[PDB]
Image (cartoon, rainbow over all chains, first blue to last red; front, side, top):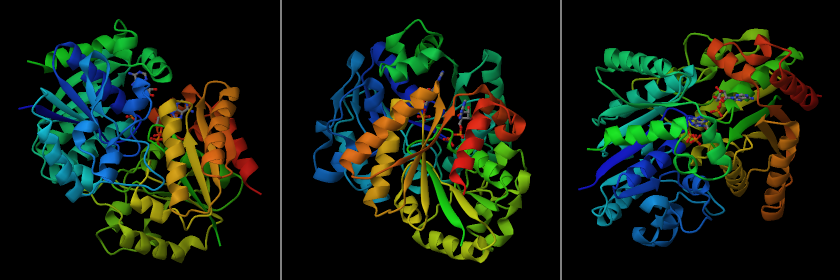
Length: 244
Length: 244
Ligand SMILES: Nc1ncnc2c1ncn2[C@@H]1O[C@H](COP(=O)(O)OP(=O)(O)O)[C@@H](O)[C@H]1O
Ligand SMILES: Nc1ncnc2c1ncn2[C@@H]1O[C@H](COP(=O)(O)OP(=O)(O)O)[C@@H](O)[C@H]1O
């Protein structure tokens, strides 16, 4: 059966979507079959980062009983994905019931992949914390800024309070120096272990790199736009270390 | 009798909290009575940016039969504010009835201010949209990035579809050149004006500035840390133009 990963964060602006897509693409390149799901319904960024014209999206599954398998889009390197959507006139969100049915139709087309990767909406919500208790791995993205780190810790506290028992792995992104990344992680590891009795791990450290910004403007993922960039190697390396 | 302003964004990481805080400080410095409310309950960032330690916050208000009046904290330059809080063993979310409670109790002190400024959670929610219709002005913050701009559009579309009659004013933050701010605004004004038949205004353009990031690490608001910085003058002049 496929391994499920949810990528999350304390707050937006930590590069969580960029990490999700570029980590998924690295997994694809190693030869795995990956389905990436943009769980930001009506506010999805996965399509934009690939520079793909908006077409059918998850929000459409909410709105026409269309089966999930027809939402599945092909991306570079054999990556499959499902977009969050541009939405209709009015706002639409997920509740626990609709989350439930979604998970059901998902396993119907899940068995094909080695990995199912969920790009979660940033931060916490009742419905998001509900979704997160089922996954095998929870990735938590943070940067070295105090706001991002404080919010990452809160997020881990809430997922834990809401009975998530999944292993938490930290991705320290936008690190200035490699030591700085380890020290961000030590701080988070200290507070989670002492206050929550929760032992977390470091998935990897991604440096601050202009290539990322360049990749976003040009709408071409950085691991593909420049595989030799520092961030690109850091993410390829993270994926390699994660995979068996 | 105060004027109410909700500062919103399509996605996090656009500088919204920094803009909310530094714009409020500029208004207070012009001599107005300002109350800033951090609506990111359980994930408050305003305390952090100010370098002030915890104290009571919305997270203590939520569960614990306590009047908003007692959450008011004194910030620099005579700014008053209410912190979102660090939580809370468990996640807690504003629902329709808690918003009513909030807005009701808010009327007990609203009278003592010229401006109430709500630093809203980023993105949309059924709850946020219910909150955003008792406000006079909606500021929408974006950067020149395509993800940020697309999300800002969708947020404006959602607020408009939910019956919001308030004028939308855009803040383009992290502009590389002042001209890029106009390029960003022109695109947004275009798609909103042609598709939604909604006339939006430019509140101002804030340049990319290392000073901002320095202010976050130093936990001292950038307009106070260095009043001469480019971003600091931009925000000060934005507030001057907005105030009577
Ligand atoms: N490693 C990095 N180096 C430089 N900029 C980065 C890096 N990671 C992320 N960013 C910047 O952060 C912005 C927001 O990234 P995004 O993936 O949208 O984050 P989130 O999903 O956390 O909001 C990007 O558009 C880019 O400017
Ligand atoms: N004008 C700017 N110049 C440089 N960096 C900025 C600017 N505005 C925001 N930032 C950066 O963006 C980060 C996130 O800002 P924040 O106010 O927390 O955004 P949001 O509330 O939209 O998530 C800041 O800590 C800082 O690194």
